[PDB]
Length: 95
Length: 51
Length: 274
Ligand SMILES: *[C@@H]1O[C@H](CO)[C@@H](O[C@@H]2O[C@H](CO)[C@@H](O[C@@H]3O[C@H](CO)[C@@H](O)[C@H](O)[C@@H]3O)[C@H](O)[C@H]2NC(C)=O)[C@H](O)[C@H]1NC(C)=O
Ligand SMILES: *[C@@H]1O[C@H](CO[C@@H]2O[C@H](CO)[C@@H](O[C@@H]3O[C@H](CO)[C@@H](O)[C@H](O)[C@@H]3O)[C@H](O)[C@H]2NC(C)=O)[C@@H](O)[C@H](O)[C@H]1NC(C)=O
Image (cartoon, rainbow over all chains, first blue to last red; front, side):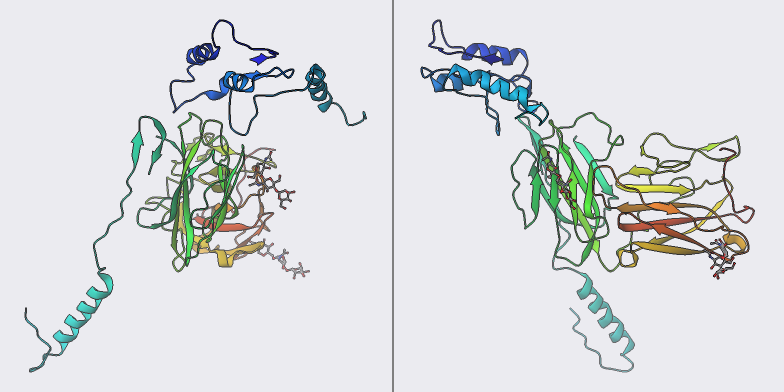
């Protein structure tokens, strides 16, 4: 799941319970012998200065040595990230 | 319970044999009996076996 | 039950060098009694070294949870440096996304009688090899056959290479049913160099007919570089003592050889193939 919310001021409840339902359908939050934690990944990108970081963090996923929560200054960085990702696979020829 | 240390007529070979047997007994027998335990346990909530 | 990976043969009458449980998701491990790790997504390395007058005899690693994958498809455990028969080896094991824990016990035997002839032979070697598998023969020419249930690799024509329980095995060349096993020879670590040779009797009832080689060797990679073992000259009836040389890309740690004799043999064995 990739989410590009600029706001997320809640209106109609919190989306934590539905994440719990989603991971219960896939048998993720029920056993520790087979956690199966890697079959669902939620990435949330923060845009603008009106972001609530704790709500985004509680909405996204958390696995060690990995970052699932991001934040950018402007919308320009949003496509800067993906243009850089495109250019990563390009040959070293271009400047 | 006997406490015999040789002495007599030809009481030499037996004393040597009993003393060498006692020496082997002391050399081989440890201060205790064999004890090597491998105790494991398993939990219904933990996948690993804690040994 | 767990996934048990074995290097060498377990002995019930020996002692263990050490025993520790390792969390494979830990970064890095806990240095238990003074041994270092290297843990990655795809590798787990233990740079174990002992301070006792003994030689490593076996290694057993138990991985949890049990995952239904055959262990004979590829290789998982190997001592990158040293190995069985030495006092220390850099033990490398490759992990999986499901395995999260490990339990490593290592066994050592006194350096005085540091031999493995008493465990790799068994009761009757006539029908059962070191691997514990029975011998199978064919009626086309009354000779042996081939096994295809373990990990094997080839480099040139008519080259046999087997790998099981850390054992690397080869046969030169083939064995007949009527042949009678005579004896075996062992090579210690102190007698191992980059290149070395052997001398065997080849007279009267000791006419060489078939030989097999089992060994423990190091690896610099997951894919090993097999030693170039080739026979020199002809083991004919004239030369009373037959010899065989070994050329090694990687230093060996242990070597075991079994001798098969048949006076009626002609000294050459090869199928009608080209
Ligand atoms: C994951 O971590 C493992 C170690 O736990 C890495 O394996 C190690 O990788 C290095 C570099 O690839 C190997 O070093 C080599 O040393 C020889 C010595 O002469 C040198 O000639 C080579 O050029 C190379 O530098 C090292 O041997 C190897 N260790 C084992 C046990 O295989 C692995 O590369 C890591 N994977 C990553 C970072 O993707
Ligand atoms: C049993 O020995 C076989 C012969 O030994 C090899 O060949 C010659 C003799 O045929 C050996 O001496 C050489 O002789 C040459 C003359 O023909 C000399 O010019 C040379 O300097 C040397 O003295 C030789 O040392 C020996 N080895 C080699 C590599 O040639 C041999 O053919 C059989 O294979 C062997 N049986 C075995 C190994 O089972």
